[PDB]
Image (cartoon, coloured by chain):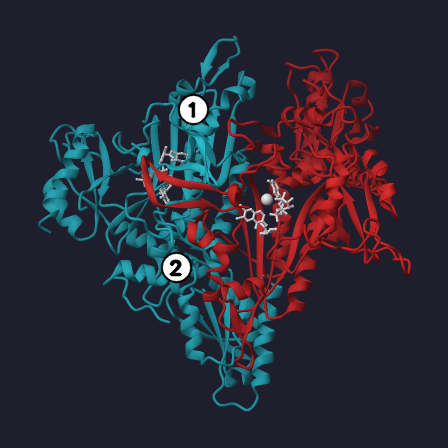
Chain colours: A cyan, B red
């Protein structure tokens, strides 16, 4: 088992190979659904634990609402173009249901229908809820393991506040928790930003977003969402509270979500030609121990040594595996565990046993270092930190190198052709969005190739005071990130 | 609000009132589906964190398998929900929502298991399933959708598998007893009540005194090679000989929450084992003057700090809209284990008043020691709840030798322990005759308990008169 396609040459097939052979997923006889094996789900558990800790600090309470929602309830607020993606239960056994029932594609209509019962006065606020659940969307866009799946795991938070300031504050708090969840657990850098009027969630006042970029195929991917919903849903669902004068006021809402797409983003960011590369924080085993016998008499000495090292790491709660299987060569094992993304390999040969040393090898850059057994615990600890740092830094470099700043449309296509995004001064007129889509599609016929507004970044470079929009020529308001996406 | 029906007098309405007014659930416009509000879901998270910790000591690895299973792979029948449409178009073939995941997982087990080095395979899922139940649903107890976990393992032999079966069963015991303060009885299902694909089903049974109802609390099966043969799950042993795997499966649902409520709830509302209550303590201030307000606020906050510094989550109810009485009632209703009242008189003593939820005992405590006496109290409450429940379980069993004795016992809201021949045949006979004489009156074999009383040398079966093999538990259920 080896990775047959190179990441830069054939990214799609490299991806499918990596995720199957590293034992993250199995494919399934229902298109767009994938089995999450222990190695994948472990990553989900880690980020889940982190995120739970941090939102409980914000006093968000977990909850669980039904998987099913009635047609009447799901469809109450007009359509507001999701309808072909709804999966419908039409019967139980061989008996038709009087009315069909939908599986949740998200929980707005389920939760907000009961919010008025729970919110009567200003004394009931804020209301802060989260769910860890599964949803179903029958994606017609190309399904891709983790990135776009028809059933996926995720978290949805919904809150309601007495005013705008408090809700918006929470929207950005959540957003930085997403930043930390990418950075600290997946070693993935993201760009924070505000979605254009064309790209935001229809029900939202504004949509803030974390964007990632896969440099290897030049594609941006939305990494997480955090919305200021204002009073839009409060009006739709009649969610009001009597204020301190017993005057009825609309709540100010937020919602926010992040999915197993994250695992996908992480795989694509750090994976190399040898396979999966895991940040230590989301790998079950931090270290693999591999014995080496240069045709040596005593297997048992080396075995006992290896065992000692394993006990040292395990006792320090650094989980590890000792691969003592007789039926595979050391080289086989090196490759096998590289493919599975074990952050550190420790090799023990006969020479090492004589010197009370061992050889430590980093998954990320393949650097080796002979070190004394009695120092392995401190070395390992530090190395697991270094690895994370390295991964993050490398990813950040690629991210920063993927942003070409431009001032006129004339520079754009070149940039797109080099698998980059563009940062451009933009008038933000809603009409220009589809225009820019159409033109970049058309011009891509020569080189979907359309580029779209990814986000208005929080980190704006200086805007020269007479600067014009790259596209319309009108006055430019802010810098916007554009690029091709998933 | 308060509880309008008494537990002993009208159990159903009491239960409905308690779950809604203590803010555990909201009813929903699809029958048998219930919203889990933060207080119920918190309970679920606690027992989940515990179970995860323990199965992870057994090298069980969590995973997630799809909600959907194809018609082919799936093939009880009318209980499955079918998705047949996306938007306005029909799926070319209908897909089911999982009622359980045996066919989803065991289909892929052959690919993952090649040799004894791949064994044991130990997987768990925290997920949801849907079963379209015929019976009227009961919040937590029997719901159309429920959360649960499913564990599935495959071992190289019978011995290892069976040992895992009972390790898991004990973990369920601890789930109920150390976290929900509910006593259970370990037993083995009769040959008609067991899981069909199983070699044997082990089970934990609970009982509700007040309505005389037995509830299956959790399951742990030895599956032997049944599924290994039907699904072709084989491993190369250490001599390169192919052998069938020996499998196990086990599960426990949000029903456990129900079992706890019913067990500990009283006529003031919810009663919670301290470890599954978000707030262990509510601190309530008591005023006379506007002058007192500051000194009592500070003091209160001080207590708060102490508790929270010792990782004891608590709520200071400094609301002015409400009287201390209303507060007491409100937080008792929501099942907070401890109430610390702080008044002026207490303030002059550097003391306060601590009040227990389970038995309403009050006592004065000096600020300096509040921490230590709260910790102890939280232990004591759990213990008291468990012990009391245990008594009520023990007094719920009536040992009989002939069917002559059964019926009075049943009608006293009891279950019977009887010597039985374990003839599958006798199982529906007994049920047809027990109800002849919104829930059924029939009684069924609950479990053949692991702790067997001695069987007198030639004792006859309480029903068929044939020789008795073992002592079995019989009773009414949901
Ligand atoms: N099918 C999917 N599988 C996995 N993750 C998804 C899927 N659809 C959306 N997400 C992610 O879920 C988060 C919440 O997304 P949401 O607001 O529901 O996205 P959306 O409106 O559907 N945008 P789109 O990706 O174009 O479908 C986003 O950060 C997406 O990255
Ligand atoms: N509808 C339900 N809601 C909640 N818990 C349930 C439900 N059905 C079964 N359980 C519990 O889930 C656990 C696993 O049992 P399982 O084998 O899945 O069902 P079961 O034994 O067939 N129960 P039943 O269908 O009522 O005869 C047991 O503790 C059951 O009591
Ligand atoms: O799901 C959303 C908005 C937000 N819901 C809570 C978590 C964070 C998330 O961004 C946008 N969205 C995305 N896909 C959908 C698909 C269908 Br089908 C429906 Cl009915 C509705 C939707 C839908 O509302
Ligand atoms: O669900 C089971 C057996 C075990 N599955 C894994 C966890 C523990 C549990 O006891 C029994 N069971 C109960 N109800 C079912 C309903 C339907 Br519909 C189907 Cl198809 C199958 C079943 C079914 O197999
Ligand atoms: Mg979408
Ligand atoms: Mg059933």
| Residue B353, x across and y down, in percent | 80, 26
- What is the chain letter for disc 1? A
A177 relative to B1 in the view: left or right: left
| Residue A96, x across and y down, in percent | 44, 35
Mark 1 crowdedness (10 Å alpha carbons): few <14, some 14-19, many ≥20: few
Which is nearer the eye, B82 or A107?
B82
Counting labels gives 2
| Residue B234, x across and y down, in percent | 52, 70
Do the numbered discs 1 and 2 sit on residues whose CB atoms are within 8 Å? no
Label 1 residue SS = helix
Q: Which mark is residue B62?
A: none
B302 relative to A423 in the view: left or right: right
Query: Does A416 sit above or below residue B307?
Result: below
Residue A334 is drawn in which quadrant?
bottom left
Q: Is mark 1 within 8 Å of ligand 3?
A: no
- Residue A257 visible? The answer is yes
A277 relative to B300 in the view: left or right: left
Residue B151 is drawn in which quadrant?
bottom right
Query: Does B124 sit above or below residue B378?
Result: below
Residue B35 is drawn in which quadrant?
top right
Mark 2 crowdedness (10 Å alpha carbons): few <14, some 14-19, many ≥20: some
| Quadrant including the N terminus of chain A | bottom left
- What is the chain letter for disc 2? A
Q: Residue drawn 83% across and 56% down?
A: B466
Label 2 residue SS = helix
Q: Which mark is residue A390?
A: 2
The image quadrant where one finds ligand 5 is top left
In the rendered structure, which disc, 1 or 2, sits on the residue that comes first in sequence? 1
Residue position for label 1: A165
């Amino acid at each position: 088992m080896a990775i047959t396609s190179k990441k830069i040459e054939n990214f799609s097939d490299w991806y499918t190979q990596v995720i199957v052979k590293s034992e993250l997923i199995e494919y399934y006889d229902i298109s767009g659904c994938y089995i999450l094996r222990p190695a994948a789900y472990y990553i989900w558990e880690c980020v889940q634990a982190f995120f739970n800790k941090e939102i409980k600090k914000l006093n968000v309470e977990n909850s669980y609402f039904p998987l099913f929602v009635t047609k009447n309830k799901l469809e109450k607020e007009k359509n507001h173009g999701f309808s072909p993606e709804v999966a419908w239960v039409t019967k139980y056994g061989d008996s038709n249901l009087p009315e069909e029932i939908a599986i949740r594609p998200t929980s707005e209509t389920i939760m907000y229908s009961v919010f008025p019962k729970w919110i009567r006065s200003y004394r009931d606020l804020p209301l802060k809820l989260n769910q860890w659940n599964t949803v179903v969307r029958w994606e017609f866009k190309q399904p891709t393991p983790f990135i776009r799946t028809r059933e996926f795991l995720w978290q949805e938070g919904h809150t309601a506040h007495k005013n705008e300031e408090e809700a918006v504050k929470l929207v950005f708090d959540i957003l930085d928790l997403y930043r930390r969840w990418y950075e600290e657990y997946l070693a993935v850098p993201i760009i924070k930003g505000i979605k254009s009027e064309g790209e935001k969630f229809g029900g939202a006042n504004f949509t803030s977003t974390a964007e990632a970029f896969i440099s290897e195929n030049g594609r941006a991917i939305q990494a997480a969402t955090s919305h200021y919903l204002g009073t839009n849903f409060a009006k739709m669902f009649k969610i009001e509270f009597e204020d301190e004068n017993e005057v009825k006021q609309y709540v100010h809402q937020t919602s926010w979500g992040c999915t197993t797409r994250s695992i996908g983003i992480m795989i694509m960011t750090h994976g190399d030609d040898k396979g999966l590369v895991l940040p230590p924080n989301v790998s079950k085993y931090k270290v693999v121990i591999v014995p080496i016998f240069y045709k040596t008499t005593d297997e048992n000495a080396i075995h006992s040594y290896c065992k000692d090292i394993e006990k040292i790491l395990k006792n320090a709660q650094i989980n590890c595996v000792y691969d003592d299987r007789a039926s595979y060569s050391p080289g086989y094992k090196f490759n096998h565990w590289e493919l599975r993304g074990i952050p550190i390999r420790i090799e023990v040969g006969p020479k090492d046993l004589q010197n009370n040393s061992c050889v430590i090898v980093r998954r990320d850059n393949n650097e080796k270092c002979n070190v004394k057994k009695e120092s392995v615990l401190l070395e390992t600890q530090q190395m697991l930190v270094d690895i994370h740092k390295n991964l993050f830094l490398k990813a950040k470099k690629k991210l920063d190198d993927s942003i070409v700043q431009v001032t006129s449309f004339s520079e754009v296509m070149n940039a797109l052709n080099k698998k980059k995004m563009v940062l451009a001064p933009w008038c933000e007129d809603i009409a220009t969005e589809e225009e820019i889509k159409k033109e970049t599609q058309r011009l891509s016929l020569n080189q979907s190739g359309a580029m779209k507004p990814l986000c208005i970044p929080l980190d704006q470079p200086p805007m020269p005071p007479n600067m014009k929009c790259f596209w319309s020529g009108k006055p430019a308001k802010r810098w916007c990130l554009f690029g091709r996406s998933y």
